[PDB]
Length: 49
Length: 431
Image (cartoon, rainbow over all chains, first blue to last red; front, side):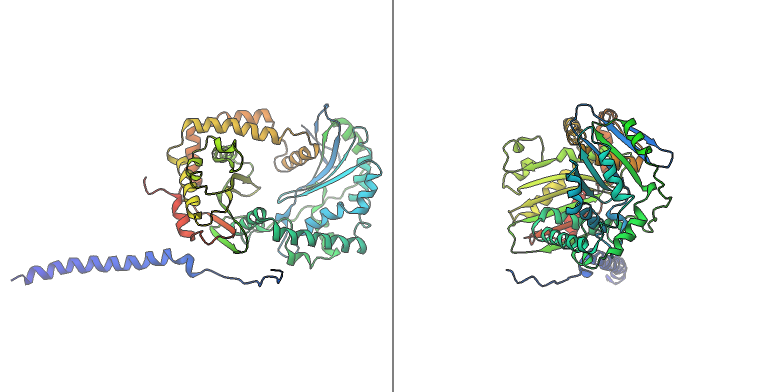
C-alpha cells in the first residue's frame, strides 16, 4: 500500500544524491591540482661529504 | 637636494652637508639585473669587479681615492670617494674610465683573472649563505618567466659562457646619457660640481635604452630545496606587495613594522610589544624572524623570513604567524598603530641620515631615476602621521585576506606541510 508514495520520495532522493556526486568530483579535482602537476629535479651531490 | 639638467643633457643631483669630512662623486645608471635575459645573466656583476680590479684600484690609490660599486635589480652605481678639496681629481678619474678610455680594462689578462674570482664568489654563496639564497629563490618562483626573477649575482651555469664581447654589447645598450644621473654627497656644493662638469665639453651620444617585452607578474607557487645534512630550516613566505610610486607605499611599510623583528638570544628583543611573541616563546618555536616590504619599479613583495632548529614544530610556527596577519583585516587595535608609527620614523631616520656618503649617494641616485626628484624626510614624516586604523584595514582586506602566497625553503623542511594547508590559513572561516 506504500507503492505510490515510495516512488515519489525516490525521485527526490536520486536527483539530490546524483547532484552531490557530480559536485564532489569537481571539488576533489580542484584541491588535488597542486599535487598532480608537481615536478622533481635531481642534481647528484658532490663527493665531499 | 638640488637637481639640474645641463645643456648637453646630463642630470646632476647634489646633497650638500657642510659637517662632513669626505665627499663622494659617482654615476648611477637605471638598468639592473632585471634588464637581462637568461643567457647573459651576470654581466652586471662582472662589470662591477672590472671596475674594482687591482690595476684600476692602484691608479686611484696613488691619488688618495677609494672605489665602490653596487648592483641591484633596478640600478647600478660606480662611486669615487676623496677628501673635500680633491673633487676635481675624482672627476678626472671617472672621466678616463667611462668616457675616454675603456679598452684597457677589458684586456684578456685582466678579464680571465676577474672571471675566475667572480666564479669563486658565487660558488661560495650557493653553499654557505642560507638565509640569503632562500630569499633569492623566493624572487625566482614568485616572478617566474618574467624579468624580475633573475638573481643579481648571476648563476654558475650562465657565468661560464660569458666572453668579452658580451660586456661590450651590454655597455653599448645601457651605459647611455639618457639613462644616467651624476650624483654628489658630503662636503660638496652644487655649483662647483656643475661648473667642473661643464669645463669638459663631453659630446655624449644620444642613444636610448631597449624596452622590455614582458611585464612583471606574481604567481602563487613554491620551491623546496631539501637537505637533511644541515642543522636548521630556513623559510621565506610572501604575498604581492606595492611598487615604488604607489599610494599605499607607506601603509605597507607600517604594517610590516607591527610584527617587526625578533632575536631569541637577546634579552631586550623578548620584551617587545608584539602579540606574536606570546605564542612562540612558550615552546621556543624559532631562533629569529623579520618582516619586510620590498618595492620595485613594477611590483613588490610583503612577508617574513625565519630560521629554526625546532624541526618537529614547523607547522605551529607558520600557523601562529598567519593567524596574526588575519587580525589586520578585522581586529587591529589603536595602540599597535601608534607604536608602529614611532618605530617606522626611527627606522628610516637611521637609513637616510647615516654618516656614510656612499650610502647616501646610492639612495639619492636611485630615486631621481624613477621620480625625477627626491622626497624630503620632513614630508615623509607627515604622511606617516596621517595613517589611521581604517587605512590599515582597507589595505589588508585587498592585499592579505584570502590571497595567493609564494614559499621557499631549505634545510630540514620535512615538517613543512603542503601548499593548500598554508594557503587556507589566509582567511579565518569565522567571518
